[PDB]
Image (tube, rainbow, N blue to C red):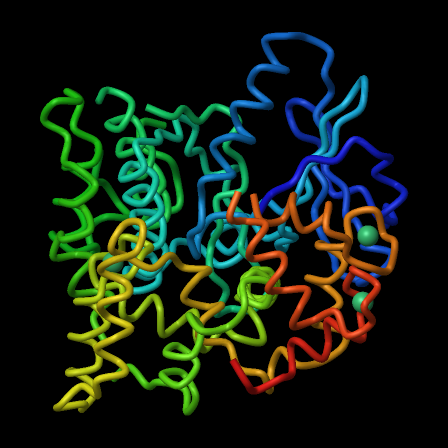
Amino acid sequence: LILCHSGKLEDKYIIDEKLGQGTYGCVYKGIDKVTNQLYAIKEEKKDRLKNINRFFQEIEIMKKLDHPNIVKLYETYENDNYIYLIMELCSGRELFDSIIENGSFTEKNAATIMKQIFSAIFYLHSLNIVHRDLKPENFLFQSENKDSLLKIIDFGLSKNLKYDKKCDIWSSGVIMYTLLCGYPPFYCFYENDWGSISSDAKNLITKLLTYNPNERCTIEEALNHPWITQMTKSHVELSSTLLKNLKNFKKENELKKIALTIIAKHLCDVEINNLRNIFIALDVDNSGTLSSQEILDGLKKIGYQKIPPDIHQVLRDIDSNASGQIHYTDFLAATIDKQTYLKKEVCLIPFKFFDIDGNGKISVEELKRIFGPLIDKAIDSLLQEVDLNGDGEIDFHEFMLMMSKLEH
Ligand SMILES: [Ca+2]
Ligand SMILES: [Ca+2]
Ligand SMILES: [Ca+2]
């Protein structure tokens, strides 16, 4: 769902502010002229080929990622001198900012952070991706709120395909050590600030910072370490419409399904952070994806005894999909409620994405790009149901009606 454009960036976005300076170019705050959504825009100067090759390597990696702790990539632009990434806008709050102010984290609060970092590494490694550059500067809190999740915001040195995995593990140990005592390691040495920190924490740090890569613990081992399990131990409460929406998602038309996915991608950390929190609570192996078993066990834990046949059908649909699991954004798309999304300002977001040339109408050529043969069948069915004009295209009024109709 991540398209590349060749037009002028500034035709779609207002550049509202410069946010900072990266190694390969600046980052700006951008505002979509039509939807008024805010993004971070990462500018990468195509000055040298070694760098240019990194830029596209990063783009190909980021297209694969969908995780609560990983920054979203929405689209890209490219001209002669630059490549631009249109990305999720986070806060400017760095991981160690509170240490500058208040000192070292408590172990409970440090564990909350480490669980998120470990989960992201696990997710990446499970995709056969190594980050290779997990320095503290590559993280940002998604918002200024104290409840904010942490996000990895840069994948410039990441590689799709180990000694590399062990380096990611090592990097996480450096961060953990710093969170707990307020200074970096080697500038495992437990001294005046460590006299009060738990033996569980020391043991984990010891496993993460093992000098010989081959004796270093795996990401699975870190996640299952007593320090993580004990300190972050907490019960899950479904929303009132969650299961209804979940079982209904599959029967929606293909355009509405994509629209909900785009909407979910924009609201995940605010309007629907309830659903995000439910996803995370259900994902007990912290893999960033849900198996049918996680959902079943989760429901049983909640109090459901005899699972209704229509929920069993959802479970089987998950088992039998592309992989046997449901991704983070797909779960959000399937659970989000019309009370949240059925608003012109929200629905305009996916409409503007579909309406590539900004015509005000979605054409067949645009749908052909959107739907990745029998794809022509789907487009035909779509237009038969949605094009109440007969003009062969979908305008915003027709789109809003499609989003609001109850009949499958
Ligand atoms: Ca999982
Ligand atoms: Ca158009
Ligand atoms: Ca029409």
Task: Report the number of discs.
Answer: 0
**What residue is at 72 percent from the left and 27 percent from the top?**
83
333 or 87, nearer to the observer: 333
Q: Is residue 247 left or right of residue 203?
A: right
Q: Which residue appears at 18% of the width and 46% of the height?
A: 222
Splitting the image into 4 quarters, where does residue 403 fall?
bottom right
Q: Position of residue 11 (x, y in %)?
A: 90, 43
Residue 86, position as x, y percentages in the image: 69, 43
Residue 31 in sight in this render: no
| Nearer-the-camera pick, 286 or 351 | 351
Instruction: Say if residue 280 shows up in the picture.
Output: yes
The one nearer the camera, 130 or 57, is 57
Extreme residue in the top direction: 49
Q: Is 17 in front, or is 47?
A: 47
Could you tell whether 9 is left or right of 233 in the image? Answer: right
**Is 278 displayed left or right of 320 in the figure?**
right
User: Measured along the vertical axis of the image, is residue 124 above or below residue 345?
Assistant: above
Residue beneath the point at 68% across and 64% down: 383
Quadrant of the rendered image containing residue 239: bottom left
Horizontal relation, residue 104 to residue 45: left or right:
left
Q: Residue 99, how many percent across, how many down?
A: 47, 52
The answer to whether 355 is drawn above or below residue 158 in the figure is: below
**Relative vertical location of residue 231 with respect to residue 92 in this rendering, above or below:** below
Where residue 229 appears, as percent x and y from the top left, is 16, 62
Q: Residue at x 23, y 20 (%)?
A: 163
Q: Quadrant of residue 204?
A: top left
